[PDB]
Amino acid sequence: KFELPELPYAYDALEPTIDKETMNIHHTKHHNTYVTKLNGALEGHEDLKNKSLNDLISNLDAVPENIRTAVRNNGGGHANHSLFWKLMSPNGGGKPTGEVADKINDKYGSFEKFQEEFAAAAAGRFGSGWAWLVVNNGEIEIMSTPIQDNPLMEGKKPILGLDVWEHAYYLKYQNKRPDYISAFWNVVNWDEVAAQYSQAA
Amino acid sequence: KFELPELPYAYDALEPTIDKETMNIHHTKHHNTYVTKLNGALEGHEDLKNKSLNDLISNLDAVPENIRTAVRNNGGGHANHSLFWKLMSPNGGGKPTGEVADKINDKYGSFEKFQEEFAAAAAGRFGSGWAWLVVNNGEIEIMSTPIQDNPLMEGKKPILGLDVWEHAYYLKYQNKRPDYISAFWNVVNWDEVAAQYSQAA
Ligand SMILES: [Mn+2]
Ligand SMILES: [Mn+2]
Ligand SMILES: [Zn+2]
Ligand SMILES: [Zn+2]
Image: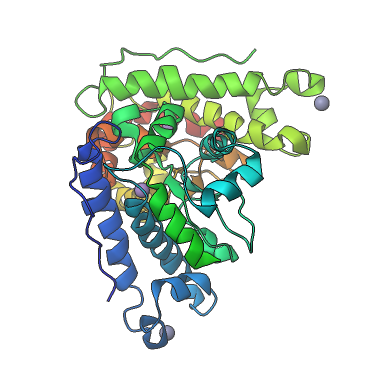
């Protein structure tokens, strides 16, 4: 029921920023694994096996203790990475657009301002985890979920996130995470962020 | 007061198993950073600045909330990695020796038995973290501390640990952690484990 999604672009379609090589691994390895561990946990747990990844991820209570964690770590990863793949593009980057843009300025004053905040957050997260641009009600803040936890698990709808696990950049940038973070901006598809905004609200 | 320690061996003195390259980074980058962040936190906090890394790490309460975390994440890392560097050797590996050996058999029956347990633990830890072979009283168990937390922070004296952060192997093994884990065994210096055992007890 849960399947590994197709990359809307080539694996080298981002080769300057993120090396096609990690793209290959991070996609056909890690991610896939999550989709695997996931499907094979809900195996036999009927009522669960009938829920959307989102619902499933949201109400982490309906899942029995015995496998709650696995649906978490694997349910989140599969969800997080799923989103990630779409928040980049060979024909993307630049500055935000749409209401998302405005809101961003209403927020931290200027986009560059926001960025400086985000970059800081993405670098804040110790160990593994992700950084995001939630949308709590008519508002949007900046947070960072550890390991694979997804913000939807706290009632906050994501619209932008950045894998910060060292496996998402250690090949090309090793320990220089800020560099990886700076680079990110070039590929980020604000069109998606936009769409992901209207739906949430 | 706190300084980055010298590697008792060359950076390529483990080149078949762990690539000299990561050895260089993991040592002169990551680790160093921790020693940096550490010294620069206790800066000004007098009574603290007079404690041994161990004491300091142990009683994580005496540290004010405002910097407790930093002494943690950085205090643990600096301690963990410090130990790690010594738990390997170009002239090491093989099977355990000394009372440590016996105890190991008393424990899981056989060393290979223990290994199978350890390897499992090292692979268990989700996200970042380390796996260890604690020594609680006259006994020794197997656990895994997340991120940089160190078992000494729970009253358990370490004698063996394995960096499991993806930065300790992603260069040579990428996502194949079990392989990295298997490989580990070859370099592990049981002589050290031994010594580290007598002292604890
Ligand atoms: Mn990832
Ligand atoms: Mn490390
Ligand atoms: Zn069930
Ligand atoms: Zn003080």
